[PDB]
Amino acid sequence: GAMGDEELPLFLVESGDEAKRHLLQVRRSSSVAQVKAMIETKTGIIPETQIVTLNGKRLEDGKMMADYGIRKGNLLFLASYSIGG
């Protein structure tokens, strides 16, 4: 509606392969649920299994980027659940 920057950039670093890098713009107030929603739009990995991690912190449900005190174009580490057993 008017001039103003709300959304904030981000950096996706695949844990399995550092070569896989993807910069995505998402609001800080955006919760990991919506943020990861985009992460799926680019990677395709189901959210329920997508384990993202901020600066030493783990991405929880309902938690917003701002909750982690992130910054414009903050670093994010992408991960995925494993079998183990």
Image (tube, rainbow, N blue to C red):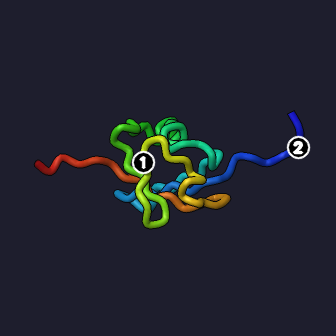
In the picture of the structure, the residue carrying the numbered disc 2 is 3
> What residue sits 43% from the left and 66% below the top?
56
Spot the residue most to the right: 2
x, y percent for residue 75: 54, 62
Q: Mark 2 is on which residue type?
A: Met
Q: Mark 1 is on which residue type?
A: Glu
> What is the spatial separation of the Cα atoms under label 1 and label 2, in whole angstroms?
32 Å
Q: Is residue 65 left or right of residue 5?
A: left
Question: Which mark is in front, 1 or 2?
Answer: 1
Instruction: Give the quarter of the figure containing the N terminus.
Output: top right
Q: What kind of element bears circle 1?
A: loop
> What residue sits 55% from the left and 54% below the top?
67
Spot the residue most to the left: 85
Return the disc, 1 or 2, that comes first in the chain's sequence. Answer: 2
> What residue sits 54% from the left and 52% below the top?
22
Spot the residue most to the bottom: 56
In the picture of the structure, the residue carrying the numbered disc 1 is 60
x, y percent for residue 55: 48, 65
> What residue sits 50% from the left and 46% below the top?
63
Q: On screen, 82 above or below 56?
A: above
